Image 1 (cartoon, rainbow, N blue to C red):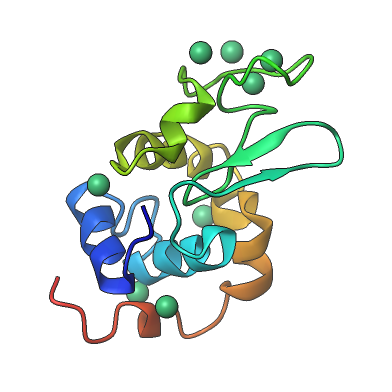
Image 2 (image 1 turned 180 degrees about the vertical axis):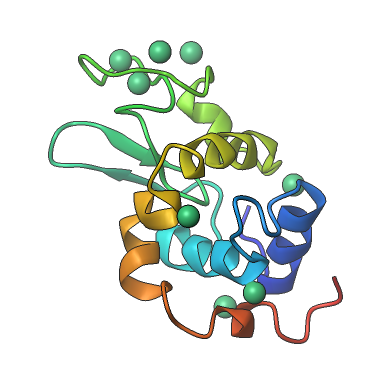
Length: 129
Ligand SMILES: [Cl-]
Ligand SMILES: [Cl-]
Ligand SMILES: [Cl-]
Ligand SMILES: [Cl-]
Ligand SMILES: [Cl-]
Ligand SMILES: [Cl-]
Ligand SMILES: [Cl-]
Ligand code: NA
């Protein structure tokens, strides 16, 4: 599923991401924009052989099981395929664990490089929330 901007903001809010670990909704929408362009089915292979999955490009090295990432963990206790669903529940629940891991949203390199410190509220501007 490719979400609209405000559609994703509302879904993220419904699932409790707004201000989770102190990160406003716009931070989450911005991260999703640059990780996946709001496409739940986005995947990307990393140089190390791990794969990133879904709207927030969650990596198989630590967070999900895809059966083809040697020496990896599955800390969200889910198949990586669950991160590609039109229902963002699995992605949100796993993102909550990731953002709680110690480095906040810096876990998402694209957030650090493209969202951090910017006017992230623009991502939810106009949205009925
Ligand atoms: Cl957009
Ligand atoms: Cl915001
Ligand atoms: Cl594996
Ligand atoms: Cl594990
Ligand atoms: Cl699995
Ligand atoms: Cl959803
Ligand atoms: Cl933080
Ligand atoms: Na894994």
